[PDB]
Length: 79
Ligand SMILES: [Ca+2]
Ligand SMILES: [Ca+2]
Ligand SMILES: [Ca+2]
Image (tube, rainbow, N blue to C red; front, side, top):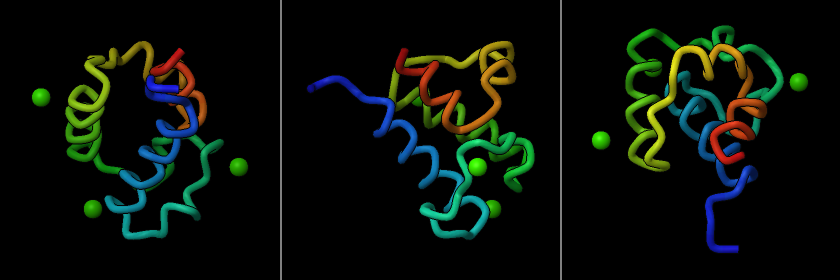
């Protein structure tokens, strides 16, 4: 499949968060609230910009906090 997939989006988010908080991406828990992962508000701005560059989607506050886990956010960005 050519289009960006949910597994790819999940991996991209784990890698992004892992780099921001200094942890292995494989250890990033995809079911916990993203506000509990150790990200800063500056991180949120940067990650939103990077998601827009990757997907062309400008994430709204509403969508993001209604899908507040890596796995639910990834699913909603793609789907
Ligand atoms: Ca950091
Ligand atoms: Ca979990
Ligand atoms: Ca841009």
